[PDB]
Length: 96
Length: 96
Ligand SMILES: [Zn+2]
Ligand SMILES: [Zn+2]
Ligand SMILES: [Zn+2]
Ligand SMILES: [Zn+2]
Ligand SMILES: [Zn+2]
Ligand SMILES: [Zn+2]
Image 1 (tube, helix red, strand yellow):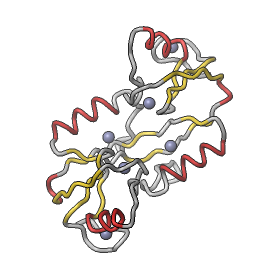
Image 2 (cartoon, chains in turn green, blue):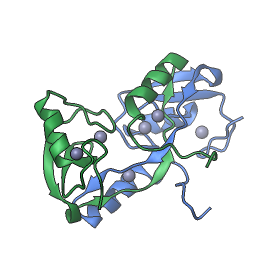
Image 3 (cartoon, rainbow over the protein chains, first blue to last red):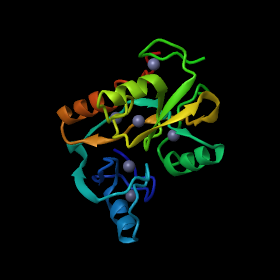
């Protein structure tokens, strides 16, 4: 039982983004696509196409590591964070 | 003071991979490049070129999040882990 944080309903069919391979509620993925959005809602990579996938057909990587990408200005680092990390889950910190 | 885990010496000049933006000991990055390696040693993305960067000129993203990429077989997930995660730092786990 996984609830979609966009529509609020339990997900039974997923949309798998190609080629970044992130998954989301299928109906919301399509809706998003219909609207002209061509970026992955979670990582912002370009999306070539969306695959339909039933709940039990997927093997998800759950490895948690630091990003470690580097930027030449604090401004560019902030833009990277806004672009890449804001919908990619709660950041893990000692403050927990 | 950051020691290189390849050569073992303290790093004063970094090589910044373009476009994945990971950084490594400059001398080892070049050496690796001289050998014909065109993949980032940390994330395995293709590397277009290597930028030379002094220690204090970089702003690193330290956000720690889960990967969450999905695969259609356990075998493909394992290949992804071997390809993407083995030199990307200690995975964060409760087992700590
Ligand atoms: Zn939804
Ligand atoms: Zn993505
Ligand atoms: Zn992964
Ligand atoms: Zn080195
Ligand atoms: Zn890299
Ligand atoms: Zn980052």
